[PDB]
Length: 130
Length: 126
Image (cartoon, rainbow over all chains, first blue to last red; front, side):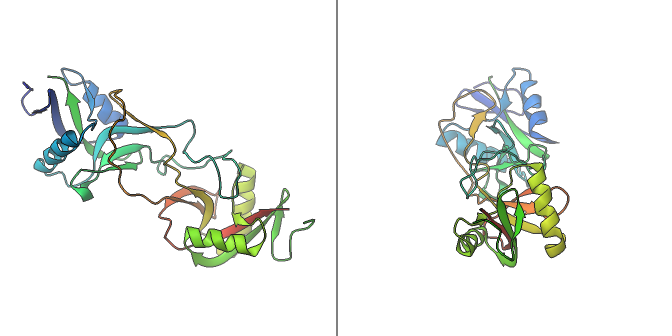
């Protein structure tokens, strides 16, 4: 309930939208370095979704913003079979083409999650304990 | 069969056909199944197959994009929160992802909306 100046309280956690363009790894790293620690925001309830969407809109973000969701895979991508039944034994996506890191979509008022290149530069939301 | 049919090229026991008609990924795939029994969108299993495909497609299409037989490249993996909490709640954007290959260099892979219309290559096993 008692957050640092600039941060907003929801359900016992503190939240803040940072208007600095970072890649997903740099934003996550930034969030871990806040005084009470923390991470890029996670969204675990309809309540949190709505709170974070309003927070981001209140801050007049005009592009997508990172959240803390990421694809974890063995290879470059997730499909294991081509249409002809054969195995995926070779992959050739560039890093620009890989889409493993999720944003809140500006086009939905920051309510829905889209996977995009991790090296994209976007503002982001951090979540910390008070 | 024993030989690749007249208009098709051979590489390691498979036959390949570059199609200079622009179709969605679905329609392109279905067209491939109608050319020959066991025909599909091209699949690529090595850098050497990619090289073959490029070598074959580049003089026909020049610098261009071809549908290839993968889809939903970002669907089947685990998605994890950085704060180490369990993914209990989902709020996905609507996506449509199908594999496009470039016809130059080494057949670079691109994500593409599956309803976009492109050139494509068919393949079947002898």
